[PDB]
Amino acid sequence: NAMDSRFLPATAFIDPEGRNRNEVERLVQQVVDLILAKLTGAAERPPMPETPITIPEAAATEATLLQAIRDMVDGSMNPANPGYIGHMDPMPATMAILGDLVAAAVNNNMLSLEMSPSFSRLETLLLRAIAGLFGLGEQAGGVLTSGGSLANLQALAVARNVAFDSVEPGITGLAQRPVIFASEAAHTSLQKAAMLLGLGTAAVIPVRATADSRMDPEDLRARIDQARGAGQHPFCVVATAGTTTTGNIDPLAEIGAIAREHGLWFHVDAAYGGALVFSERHRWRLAGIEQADSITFNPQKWLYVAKTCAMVLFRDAGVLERAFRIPAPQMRATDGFINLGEIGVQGTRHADVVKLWLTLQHIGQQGYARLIDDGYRLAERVVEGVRQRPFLRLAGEIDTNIVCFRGEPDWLPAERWDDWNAALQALLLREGKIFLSLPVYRGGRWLRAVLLNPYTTDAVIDAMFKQIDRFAG
Amino acid sequence: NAMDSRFLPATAFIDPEGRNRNEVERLVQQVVDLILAKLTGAAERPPMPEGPITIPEAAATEATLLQAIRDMVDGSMNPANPGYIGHMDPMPATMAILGDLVAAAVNNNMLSLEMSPSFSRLETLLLRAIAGLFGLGEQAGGVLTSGGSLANLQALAVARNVAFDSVEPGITGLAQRPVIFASEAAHTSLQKAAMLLGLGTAAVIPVRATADSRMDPEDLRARIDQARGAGQHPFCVVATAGTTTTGNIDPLAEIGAIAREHGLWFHVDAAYGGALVFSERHRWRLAGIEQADSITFNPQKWLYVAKTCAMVLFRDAGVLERAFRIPAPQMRATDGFINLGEIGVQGTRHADVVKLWLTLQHIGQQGYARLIDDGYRLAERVVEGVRQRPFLRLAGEIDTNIVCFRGEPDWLPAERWDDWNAALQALLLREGKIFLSLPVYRGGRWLRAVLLNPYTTDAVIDAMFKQIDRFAGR
Ligand SMILES: [Cl-]
């Protein structure tokens, strides 16, 4: 009985008959007290931190373990700091923290129903409910995936399988290259997925985006015609609802109409912007999404669910059985549910439905509508700050709570603007304790604000522009 | 502005300046106390548990949320029950629970260094150490993945890219079908991977396994030769260290040698059996694994890390930059580290390294060696029990703490054996409070014991056979 031996610490596991209740309660409380201290005092740590691994033979002491946690926390990025305004990575909702505690504690497996009796059923039903908010219709549904890249991968795998019947024989027999279309501003997980799917990164054909970083439907139509002429076999168009760099939304209805005209799978990568389904004031921006063949949506971004939390939704969930699931005996439960492992890229999977369901209930649709509004308000203040300053330039109009801008100062030649913006970013972080990201975009370095932290204020944005004004004179 | 609202509960987020500190502490404490009650009393719940879903307009109350947690726990499978002896799914190490609490609190992202300054470096360094423990050499390392299926996918994607130079142009132009070889007992994530990679499920050619469910080397050589004669293009052999159903280990050194003789990528799926690296008494079972081109290993199974925790290791970690990573500017920190999203299937990714690192430190290599030995002793007790009962048959020799066996009673014709075993399994659960799984194997229904719960005892195994004896009329 290993847990009686001198070879395991008394608290290595939790005795299911309570025999080490007191000792585990103590260890758990130390971690809990420490994490809560770090989080209720998060503003004491900056948005980014200032900075010999061996697996020990013998059990580490509580002191070593607590010190490691302390060092792990102190050396981590800190989106909780009101100054953290640079990424689609938010401080987590409290119930998402607690949801993951519960999930880890019960340690169920989304691979199959018998390994996750309630969570599998909860996830299937919750995702049907969400697919309904997107307007996908009564056959719609999907699966949670560990990150949006996997959601896009699985959407693209289904589009491919549908077009080429490739589940069993593969795609190596093809005389014509399969290709997909996406905005020149669409997410890189498309190229990574295209590589993984056997299509190659070059199978993702870029469609011109406007000055406001939205896909150009006229150019979509042109690229499809060009592809056919070159003897390629288009099978999918990806529209993006909230691009990663600038946060803009493609014209989903127009793009979707073109895809449908040409018999192409219509996927909407709504990883970020999908959260607008909870805002009546803003969801008109997603008009057209209801006719998608599939949708990628990431609650871990604008719904504040602790990473990872993402899903792929299909307007006809049965497609996962016809053009994804590998040949195998089909065992459905008496209440209709199926093993989720058969119809996802992953087999074993963490129960993300716990944090998702708990966060959605604690915040509510109105809670998210208000957060979404405040996000837009903060962003509009940044837009106005940039308009007021002639040495700054916007990337273009905004569609979400994201503002990409940069310095283009006339006291420097263009070739020096990348150093100016890197330097401004460094200065804002060092002296302002304000974190902006600095993506490459349109061949240059642009500053990027993602206004997500619930505790970011007008004053933080004003502090930013004062530092920018100092840096520029 | 939102947190100063009627529209948000005072505890929806944690105020970074402490202004909701007391309310947060109490909510957290109620969930902590409830979860600890459920776990310290887990044996009160059976191994298996005995609408409509609406996203509310308004914030749920604390009472509703706590009740939902109670309902979710009570409706979940319960591997902490000493009777739960049926799957590669363990009760979690205490520090792995706590690790996920820490990871979710700081909510960093493994996608890039900038988003996980400490965790990215800790993961890269830790997996280099683990790869070294598998004996893969100085250049070896890898990445954590959300599950072993992804680890297998990534390893096969690399094998494919190396063989066919397919990162940019894909594989559609190929005139010969790419194929891989794996034991007829190997994991289905190979077929799913093969489908995903564009090879098709049928690209996975099954190799005959012995009566003890280990891959036959002679049949492997024949299948490779047959593939080449059939116009196909072999590029990878997958050996399995701990098959999912029976827990057996392919002869890794012999299979590796044959892979190498034919110039094929050698991948070892050690999802389960890779935990033997922490056991001096049993790690010889993995001999040969040190020459693998890649290894899949799942701490979430036999190292008790709460799901998910898995990795893919490469003997040359550099291969991820040459034959996987998509064309892009290479950002590299001054201390050498790279953005991990560029060299994984996933982009954004939960920080699994936290619970992995805390659990490995708390249990230690000595701890795992003890856990593993006791697993083998329980498995050996099941084997002995089966051998004593003529109406039961073992699937074959065991290589790990897994025993697959079934009834083959001579008082029934063979076509009734599936029902007998299904009835036995159902009776063990209902009457014995003992969970065995019941996979399809060799065309029939087999009982399957995975002896993982550290609180599973000889008494449990004895109770199991008592029930078995009663069901069969002694
Ligand atoms: Cl996860």
Image: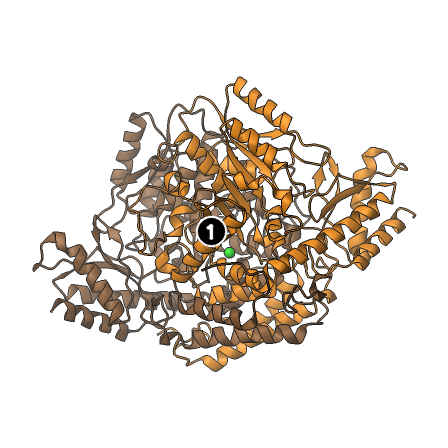
Chain colours: A brown, B orange
Provide residue B125's location: percent of width, then percent of height.
44, 55
- Quarter of the figure with the C terminus of chain A: bottom left
A219, A45: nearer the viewer = A45
Report which quarter residue A278 is drawn in: bottom left
Q: Position of residue B184 (x, y in %)?
A: 64, 33
Residue B277 x, y percent position in the rendering? 59, 50
The residue that appears at 62% across and 49% down in the rendered structure is B276
Residue where numbered disc 1 is placed = B128
Taking the spot 32% from the left edge, 28% from the top edge, the residue there is: A228
- Label 1 neighbourhood size at 10 Å, few (<14), some (14-19), many (20+)? many
Circle 1: element type: helix
Q: Give the x, y percent position of residue A304.
A: 43, 64
Q: Determine whether B57 is above or below A299 in the image.
A: below
Q: Residue at x 35, y 35 (%)?
A: B168
Figure check: A442 above or below B117: above
Q: Given the image, on which type of amino acid does mark 1 rest?
A: Arg
Compared across the picture, whether B83 is left or right of A405 comes to: right
